[PDB]
Image (cartoon, rainbow, N blue to C red):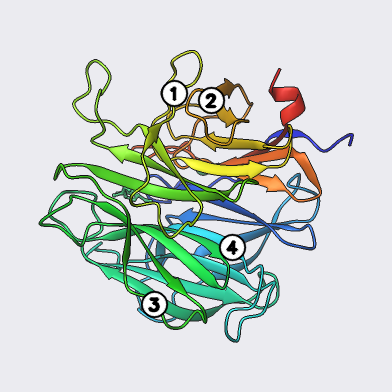
Amino acid sequence: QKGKTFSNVEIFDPPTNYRDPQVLYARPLELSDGTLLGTWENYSPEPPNVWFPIVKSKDGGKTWKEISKVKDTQNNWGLRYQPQLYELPRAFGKYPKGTVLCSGSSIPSDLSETLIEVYASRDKGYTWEFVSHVALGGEALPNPGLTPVWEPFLMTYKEKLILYYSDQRDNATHSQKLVHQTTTDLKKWSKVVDDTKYANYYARPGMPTVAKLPNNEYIYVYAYGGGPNPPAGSDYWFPVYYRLSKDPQKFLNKAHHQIVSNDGTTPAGSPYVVWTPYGGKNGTIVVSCGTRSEIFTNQALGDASAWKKWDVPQPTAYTRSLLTFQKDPDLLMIMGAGILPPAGGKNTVSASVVRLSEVMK
Ligand SMILES: OC[C@@H]1O[C@@H](OC[C@@H]2NC[C@H](O)[C@H]2O)[C@H](O)[C@H]1O
Ligand SMILES: [Ca+2]
């Protein structure tokens, strides 16, 4: 149990010539053999077309090396935004258990279109193959009236793989809404199913992440753009809300809850949720958001009155992400790739591993 924590390891410091914000949107993955993989949006000068770098750690995140790049082999655009890594926990069609997936959005350098893709690695991240196209959208700017798709998140439920994402395609009715599609083979995707939408046109629920709880329930966490009560001097904000459901295909008609910590802190922006068995029968739900450095925890299965907040040494970052370690539930990785543009040339990809038993004190 000794020597497993470490603070602010620098995974990747981009060159001066990368385009603002240079890097962003870090995502980690623990494989069944204990190795870690990571990726981020890599804003290299183009051409050549942008790619998702894949880094590997064998020592629990202390040291890293690049072992491959996921490249767009289909569109001659690049893999540009919102990567997401995922290890299959069971076979889906011809992809066995242990296959690594990388989802993300392929987008031309002019940002005229958006395309959520799935790539797969059969060798724990050394090589990649295109698998399928998921969702095509329009222009890659987060403005009302445009029709892009964004921000894929993968999770298995029973025999289905669910891919949740953000959707502006219903542009006459919702500025953006949250949706999913499912697959049983990674080839054929189900029709679009709504997960969260709001009647007010200018509402923009976005950036969905999901975690399984030990009471047969799932928690769906998102940033509710256009949510009520923007703070003084703000006409529009992105408070973190969530929903609870037994069936993670049916969040749509579940009551929303805002996350507010015991002291009144209101996380906002680009959230990320995990659950670990640490801390009791209920374990611990841990959420990060994009505007605070603290983590927010809940040891009461998502009871709205039970959120707490704790400092960690990893700085605030856009869609700062979290990872739990299968063989040690007390250990939490927090990974970030800096802030939204303008970043001032100072974003780097970094991570910390903390113990909840130390940090929750
Ligand atoms: O990831 C790069 C980033 O994506 C764009 O924003 C997407 C919006 N984020 C919250 C909403 O869910 C979505 O519409 C932004 O232009 C890029 O910097
Ligand atoms: Ca740099």
Q: Is residue 132 found left or right of 225 in the rendered image?
A: right
Q: Earlier in the sequence, mark 2 or mark 1?
A: 1
- Give the vertical position of 102 relative to 330 (above or below): below
- Is the residue indicated by label 3 positioned so its CB lies within 8 Å of ligand 1? no
Q: Position of residue 346 (x, y in %)?
A: 47, 36
Q: Which residue sits at x=58%, y=30%? A: 298
Farthest residue to the top: give it: 263
Residue at numbered disc 4: 86
Q: Which residue sits at x=35%, y=31%? A: 239
Q: Secondary structure at mark 4?
A: strand
- Tell me whether circle 2 and circle 3 mark residues in contact (CB < 8 Å): no
How crowded pointer 3 is (Cα within 10 Å; few <14, some 14-19, many 20+) is rated as: some
Which image quadrant is residue 139 in?
A: bottom left
1 or 3: mark nearer the eye = 1
Question: Tag 2: residue type?
Answer: Trp
The alpha-carbon separation of the residues under discs 2 and 3 comes to 38 Å
Question: Tag 4: residue type?
Answer: Tyr
- Tell me whether circle 1 and circle 3 mark residues in contact (CB < 8 Å): no
- Tell me whether circle 2 and circle 4 mark residues in contact (CB < 8 Å): no
As drawn, the label of residue 133 is 3
Q: Is residue 213 found left or right of 49 in the rendered image?
A: right
Residue at numbered disc 1: 260
- Tell me whether circle 4 and circle 3 mark residues in contact (CB < 8 Å): no
The foreground one among 216 and 227 is 216
The alpha-carbon separation of the residues under discs 2 and 1 comes to 7 Å
The foreground one among 173 and 335 is 173
Q: Secondary structure at mark 3?
A: strand
Q: Earlier in the sequence, mark 1 or mark 3?
A: 3
Residue at numbered disc 2: 307
As drawn, the label of residue 58 is none
